[PDB]
Length: 86
Length: 86
Image 1 (spheres, chains in turn cyan, orange):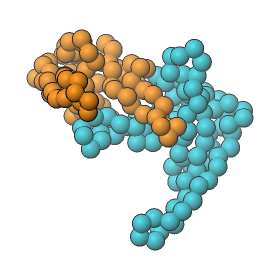
Image 2: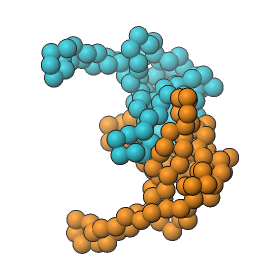
Image 3: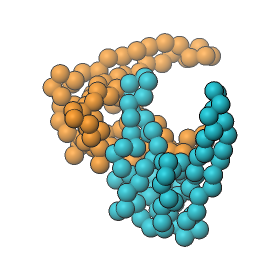
Image 4: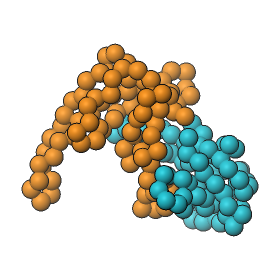
């Protein structure tokens, strides 16, 4: 399991916006977190939230299976990092 | 944890080869496996092995932390799926 932590300073999201190729508006909500990848300290990672989902609250989390998909070359990829409480 | 299985029929690797931009030869060893991504059946996934590593033997495996890295846009990515015995 990947240990992910939302620190108290990371409790909010920011929103970026724009227009798609054929005219549809979009909005993306982004939040920061720390993920322990086994180095001397955890590293900073950007999260893009799913539609209608609030920011994750401060605390410890692990990664949900729905984060993964098989990519167009047949290797596993992260689609969007989705978290669940530890 | 992601459950990965090497089936008896997936116990070998194949090798692809070529030459880099500036003349160096390379060889890549590839092996297939099944990963349970929570659908009605496990899905087929291609693995690229690290240099000097044998094919994984048939059996059950989970994913090692060294499989992940922060990508150039700040989001988490899979570098290469690396496995450890379950």
